[PDB]
Amino acid sequence: CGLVASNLNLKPGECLRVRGEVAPDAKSFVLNLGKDSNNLCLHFNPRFNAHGDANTIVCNSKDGGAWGTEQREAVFPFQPGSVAEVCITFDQANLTVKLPDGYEFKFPNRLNLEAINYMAADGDFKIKCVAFD
Amino acid sequence: CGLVASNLNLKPGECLRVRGEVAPDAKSFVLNLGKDSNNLCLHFNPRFNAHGDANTIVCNSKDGGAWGTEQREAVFPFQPGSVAEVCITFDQANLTVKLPDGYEFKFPNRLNLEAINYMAADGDFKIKCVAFD
Ligand SMILES: OC[C@H]1O[C@H](O[C@H]2O[C@H](CO)[C@@H](O)[C@H](O)[C@H]2O)[C@H](O)[C@@H](O)[C@@H]1O
Image (tube, rainbow over all chains, first blue to last red; front, side, top):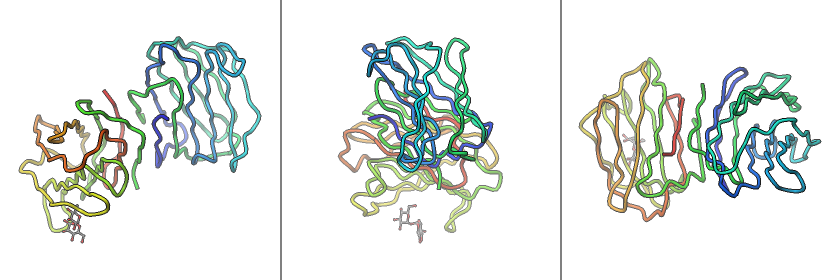
């Protein structure tokens, strides 16, 4: 189980930058962001080869412990056994997720969060650096 | 409270770097490192003006809830209203804390932790960057 962090106090428009090492055998990794582990405005799950997906990013929310509806993205600029950085911002309508190679996507802010206080990583992604601006 | 991180898995010899903004009217700040809130291999408390102390670094350990024997350092390379980075490693003998302006000191490793898995920050210090390498 990966890094867990709380009291992040990330505000709208502020950039959370996460750089890590994608494992060479990577099947999947997760970045979870929200208020706490039961209230996620972003479950960010790149799947290299996992649960029937190949090279697909699956996103979801979690509200009071209840998962929302999964959203599958159109791009996948990740490779196993490489360094990757992700950059996340939000406003009360959307999260914006910036990816390697100039790709980005928006995911609705379904919880209407005004602060992100919680982050957790899991799976085949070793975090090397977290920055808050 | 400030940032809390767990599952850091910082192994002997590896470097934890923490860069933050010291408040312009800062009185003190704290970085706590260890296993959990009751088991700290390093409580690192720069006091600008707190507890009757001026420009003093106060260090201690905490083992099973018990504060150890407090140690104070001789140098204080911190300024209110500035950016400061501290870099921490450990081996079985000591933690080595590297401060701004090239000062460093050692603090005895009083716990038998295989790794540092927990960090907590508090006080007049806004973390901007945490790196594990
Ligand atoms: O009254 C609270 C005291 O806080 C400090 O002392 C406690 O916390 C220290 C770490 O910052 C420990 O080293 C110490 O053993 C604890 O008793 C402060 O140094 C004291 O002056 C305060 O009275």
